[PDB]
Image (cartoon, rainbow over all chains, first blue to last red):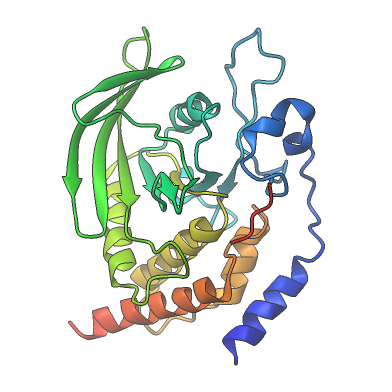
Length: 279
Length: 5
């Protein structure tokens, strides 16, 4: 009770999806979506420029910009996207490069229960790989309990002075079903993500992905938004979980998929508050 | 084809 009523009321307001998703529905973009029914809104989708002139449709990826506030800088925003398909790996790196993203949050394993959630889009440690026009070196990997950090260096093949470091925070322990029973791992992880992002000036939006780009993706993003409000305005500031979910859902449909994820968000915030009060 | 979650 209370959480179910709140989540069910949110699910009410999305029974009609109002904003247009026509680009994702185009015949040329059909096999760029992992799920037929999960598509980016046209008005917030990431439009990919500088594509191959021989490709009739080269501007599409299943991804949306998410701003936490109406006047949010790119540095304070997110990109919510699906895990790479075999044929969108190159488009994914075009997106990272174009948006100047410096931090990637991966919320899934590559494969879970025998189903691909994300095709591997990074080289092995110390290896280099070319993804279309983009070159990626994997400089170092650091294992933590819940995640692995991959320090990647991304550049455009041939062009000088385009190299930049992209930090891939790969959350590894999310359960195959349900949500973690305690938010500690996610909070410590998001704390490292945030400090990394804030330390890079002129960084672009943080890229966050899951299999569809809405469930785990929305859960991670909304928690990050809320704890950053607490970071900025203190532990007695007012927190409106439903309105925050409404805000991100106006930019990509269906963010935060299950009531367990909904309860997990509240738990994470309450833990973050408790952590600051309890030293 | 359809996102169950």
